[PDB]
Amino acid sequence: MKVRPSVKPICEKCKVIKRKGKVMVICENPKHKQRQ
Amino acid sequence: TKGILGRKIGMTQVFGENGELIPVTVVEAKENVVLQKKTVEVDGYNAIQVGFEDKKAYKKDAKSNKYANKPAEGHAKKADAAPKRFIREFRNVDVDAYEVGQEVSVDTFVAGDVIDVTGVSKGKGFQGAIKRHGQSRGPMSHGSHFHRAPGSVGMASDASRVFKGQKMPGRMGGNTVTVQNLEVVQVDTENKVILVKGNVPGPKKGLVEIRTSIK
Amino acid sequence: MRQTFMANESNIERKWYVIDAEGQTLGRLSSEVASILRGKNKVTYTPHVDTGDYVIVINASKIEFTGNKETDKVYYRHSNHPGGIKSITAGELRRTNPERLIENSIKGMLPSTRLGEKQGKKLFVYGGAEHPHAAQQPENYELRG
Amino acid sequence: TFDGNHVTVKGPKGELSRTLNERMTFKQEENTIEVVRPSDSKEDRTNHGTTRALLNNMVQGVSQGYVKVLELVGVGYRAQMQGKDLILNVGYSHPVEIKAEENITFSVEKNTVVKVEGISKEQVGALASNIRSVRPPEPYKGKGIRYQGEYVRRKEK
RNA sequence: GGGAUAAGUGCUGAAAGCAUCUAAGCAUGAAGCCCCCCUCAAGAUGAGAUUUCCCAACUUGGUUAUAAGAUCCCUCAAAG
RNA sequence: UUGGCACCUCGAUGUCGGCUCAUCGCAUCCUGGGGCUGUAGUCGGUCCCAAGGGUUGGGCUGUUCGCCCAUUAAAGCGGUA
RNA sequence: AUAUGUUAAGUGGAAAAGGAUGUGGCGUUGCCCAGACAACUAG
Ligand SMILES: [Mg+2]
Ligand SMILES: [Mg+2]
Ligand SMILES: [Mg+2]
Ligand SMILES: [Mg+2]
Ligand SMILES: [Mg+2]
Ligand SMILES: [Mg+2]
Ligand SMILES: [Mg+2]
Ligand SMILES: [Mg+2]
Ligand SMILES: [Mg+2]
Ligand SMILES: [Mg+2]
Ligand SMILES: [Mg+2]
Ligand SMILES: [Mg+2]
Ligand SMILES: [Mg+2]
Ligand SMILES: [Mg+2]
Ligand SMILES: [Mg+2]
Ligand SMILES: [Mg+2]
Ligand SMILES: [Mg+2]
Ligand SMILES: [Mg+2]
Ligand SMILES: [Mg+2]
Ligand SMILES: [Mg+2]
Ligand SMILES: [Mg+2]
Ligand SMILES: [Mg+2]
Ligand SMILES: [Mg+2]
Ligand SMILES: [Mg+2]
Ligand SMILES: [Mg+2]
Ligand SMILES: [Mg+2]
Ligand SMILES: [Mn+2]
Ligand SMILES: [Mn+2]
Ligand SMILES: [Mn+2]
Ligand SMILES: [Mn+2]
Ligand SMILES: [Mn+2]
Ligand SMILES: [Mn+2]
Ligand SMILES: [Mn+2]
Ligand SMILES: [Mn+2]
Ligand SMILES: [Mn+2]
Ligand SMILES: [Mn+2]
Ligand SMILES: [Mn+2]
Ligand SMILES: [Mn+2]
Ligand SMILES: [Mn+2]
Ligand SMILES: [Mn+2]
Ligand SMILES: [Mn+2]
Ligand SMILES: [Mn+2]
Ligand SMILES: [Mn+2]
Ligand SMILES: [Mn+2]
Ligand SMILES: [Mn+2]
Ligand SMILES: [Mn+2]
Ligand SMILES: [Mn+2]
């Protein structure tokens, strides 16, 4: 997961969710994941 | 798991089947007898108390430790043994095989058995830092007035004490040391001697406790 | 110096009580017991002497925590050796030796003065449900409020 | 079939086996029930919806259990045993031990075709998550333990 | 070797008919965290345990020698 | 770090570099665990966890730096007057 | 202590641009049993 302060969906397949108390991207593309 | 007490007699060479030259320490274990069975029942934990070398007479009315005192008399007499001069526990024995009155004998250690050996470590006196922690000396020459002193002992005004770890001069020789993994090389049942591969920490005549290796 | 009772060692009696931690919050059982221990509960309270009663806290194991702190509340300790801090223990204290979790926790609510010290030595905490001290014949006591 | 025990809403299914916790503090309905959408009060609606979901997932597999299938897309493939699948998988230089009898878990052997064969989807999902854990689907020549019907993206050497 | 964990990988899962490692609940996972390994350690005043040893004369609580047991002193060293 | 300010010390708070001894932080040089990869393999890049331990001998210069010779798994960065 | 609500971060008990279906209130609106959101079947 790219680890960044900002979190937005990357592409129109992406979905945002909290998972440990942390907001995270779920784009399904292996090189498009995120977790603030 | 097994163990015996023994007096370190000293070092020799001995020869392997391959001509291999194996340094050996000669441990001697005449006369060890089990003296007490320590069960969880009474003692709270499991141990066999073995009494090493034999010592004199009775509550005989005299100066030395060589002669046993009434407390020892009664302790040995509960075990139908003559009074002994060294006594130690081994926890981590088989605690059930071992009935109280019996001898342990050298024959319990079989050749090629790998073992750990405890014993207190020779004895240097009050000693300087270079001898006791190996610390490099200061330069000689080049105008130095520093040779065998332990270094800076601390910080400036921040660590404004000397930290509790600090290492400096004093007594060297105490401290029990055990050394791990040494082969039994031979066992000489005729004189109760038992040969140990390598060197065990004693001075000489030091009591050492051999026990079955852990790990 | 008109009138003002001060309790002597002649003029004072010390009762024994048993407390069931099972079902209680750590801090609340702790503070209630501390006042019990200081005698701050009798009308004959007097500051320069140990006026308190004995407390045996029971089933220390069943003590509880409020927050998400079975894991989040660490106890530290330092060995006075360099870098020998010891973070260890959380509500792991309640797992092994909770007798100390309750003991030290209660004792941190008594004054650090030799009197307060003797006062702390009047507590007895057992994780199990069976004190040795039956001979002192403790009365069962219910947590107020 | 339609047989299940009850007490304190922690009751075993009568067929085969069960035992499970409830979150308690919730509205409950007999047989199939419903209302995954809302119940009781507040945003505890989520929790109760998970309760109905869990018990429903429980009853759904007790008569006809669901079983994940795992295919070994490589030149090596696991054999079989009465308590293990004997995963001599991929080409790591040793066979691995695996499997457990907990609840009910069947073996499988079909030349690179294996299956967990449990009851509830949680135990199956677990033992197969780990049966598939031993080697992974490396996305080139697609090799590796693979859940059946899994997307397996690839790329160019 | 065992236990718990991080980043991570997940399972089951609603909120949010789907989907989702997570909020309930589960599994996995590091030279690191705990136990294991080595030495110290009951002045742990919270002063622990086991085995053995000794055992009265006087008393207006105590008194005094003694016992088990040591030590002083003396010959010493593996100790200093 | 270079500074700004002039609050402690002018009836004195020794000062660069080295040497001796270290101790701590993590923004990790190596080693352990992973994600992405424009990751085939062998290597690597980059981020994430991790501070247990380790982290070299010389040529020139007072030097700290720096260049260089030769090795290393690596030749980490800072605090502690 | 009382009454009514909030907060689940030990926030309380250090910090910004920026970021998030975290929850609470107060409003305004467009599609809704003429069937809509979502899911599944047909280009
Ligand atoms: Mg970052
Ligand atoms: Mg996690
Ligand atoms: Mg000398
Ligand atoms: Mg709790
Ligand atoms: Mg205990
Ligand atoms: Mg103080
Ligand atoms: Mg567990
Ligand atoms: Mg003492
Ligand atoms: Mg006492
Ligand atoms: Mg003592
Ligand atoms: Mg003399
Ligand atoms: Mg030094
Ligand atoms: Mg970086
Ligand atoms: Mg480190
Ligand atoms: Mg160290
Ligand atoms: Mg160099
Ligand atoms: Mg070179
Ligand atoms: Mg490498
Ligand atoms: Mg350098
Ligand atoms: Mg440094
Ligand atoms: Mg604070
Ligand atoms: Mg600004
Ligand atoms: Mg803010
Ligand atoms: Mg809002
Ligand atoms: Mg709102
Ligand atoms: Mg309107
Ligand atoms: Mn040197
Ligand atoms: Mn001088
Ligand atoms: Mn000199
Ligand atoms: Mn100085
Ligand atoms: Mn584990
Ligand atoms: Mn679902
Ligand atoms: Mn004692
Ligand atoms: Mn009398
Ligand atoms: Mn005598
Ligand atoms: Mn001699
Ligand atoms: Mn400055
Ligand atoms: Mn000034
Ligand atoms: Mn001014
Ligand atoms: Mn002065
Ligand atoms: Mn001065
Ligand atoms: Mn870090
Ligand atoms: Mn790595
Ligand atoms: Mn370091
Ligand atoms: Mn309220
Ligand atoms: Mn805070
Ligand atoms: Mn903002």
Image (cartoon, coloured by chain):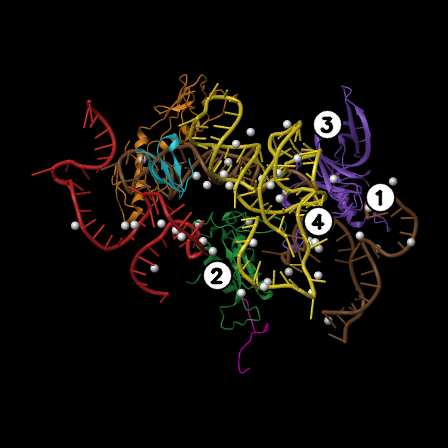
Chain colours: A cyan, B purple, C green, D orange, E brown, F yellow, G red
The magenta region covers C1-14
Distance between mark 1 and mark 2 Cα atoms: 64 Å
In the visual, does C69 lie left or right of B85?
left
Q: Label 4, on which residue?
A: B152
Q: Label 3, on which residue?
A: B110
Which badge, 1 or 4, is on the more N-terminal residue? 1
Residue B16's quadrant in the figure?
top right
Label 1 within 8 A of ligand 35 by Cβ: no
Label 4: state its secondary structure. loop
- Main secondary-structure element of the magenta-colored stretch: loop
Residue F41: horizontal and vertical position, in percent?
50, 21
Label 3: state its secondary structure. loop
Distance between mark 3 and mark 2 Cα atoms: 64 Å
- Chain hosting mark 2: C
Residue B137: horizontal and vertical position, in percent?
76, 43
- Label 4 Cα crowd, 10 Å radius (few <14 / some 14-19 / many 20+): few
The dot on residue B56 is 1
- Chain hosting mark 4: B
Residue G22: horizontal and vertical position, in percent?
33, 46
Identify which residue is drawn at 39% across, 31% down: A31
Q: Label 2, on which residue?
A: C31
Label 2 within 8 A of ligand 4 by Cβ: no
- Chain hosting mark 1: B
Q: Amino acid at mark 1?
A: Lys
In the visual, does C125 lie left or right of E22?
right
- Residue D80 in view (yes/no): yes
In the visual, does B199 lie left or right of D109?
right
Distance between mark 1 and mark 4 Cα atoms: 54 Å
